[PDB]
Amino acid sequence: AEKDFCKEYEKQVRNGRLFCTRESDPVRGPDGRMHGNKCALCAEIFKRRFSEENSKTDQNLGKAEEKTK
């Protein structure tokens, strides 16, 4: 369950980003899952989720007020 691994990684998020933990088990994922580290997998979720959710899945939110308005 990477979601749970990245769930706890959410709690470790440093500087608005999630920093991989000493525990980095390789797995295949868009960015490589753990290729460079499990953080990449979790960050992969944030990149896709946050980009999609923050934009293209929430009416832009933030810009559709004075950018996309």
Image (spheres, rainbow, N blue to C red):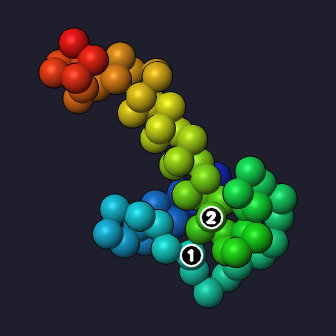
What secondary structure is found at the residue carrying circle 2?
A: helix
Answer left or right for 58 relative to 26: left
What secondary structure is found at the residue carrying circle 1?
A: loop
Which residue of the protein is positioned furthest toward the front in this rendering? 67
Percent x, y of residue 61: 28, 25
Q: Residue at x 62, y 64 (%)?
A: 40
Question: Is residue 4 in view?
Answer: no
Percent x, y of residue 44: 61, 53
Question: Pointer 1: residues within 10 angstroms few (<14), some, or many (20+)?
Answer: many
Answer above or below: position of 56 versus 16. Answer: above
Answer above or below: position of 28 versus 52. Answer: below
Question: Pointer 2: residues within 10 angstroms few (<14), some, or many (20+)?
Answer: many
Percent x, y of residue 13: 41, 67
Q: Are marks 1 and 2 in contact (CB under 8 Å)?
A: yes
Answer left or right for 35 relative to 9: right
Which one is nearer the viewer's eye here, 68 or 48?
A: 68
In the rendered image, the quadrant that contains the N terminus is bottom right
Which residue of the protein is positioned furthest toward the left in this rendering? 66
Q: Residue at x 55, y 58 (%)?
A: 43
Determine which residue is flagged by label 2: 40
Residue 64 falls in image quadrant? top left
Q: Residue at x 73, y 61 (%)?
A: 33
Determine which residue is flagged by label 1: 20
Label 1, label 2: how far apart the Cα atoms are: 8 Å
Q: Which circle's residue, 1 or 2, is located before the other in the chain?
A: 1
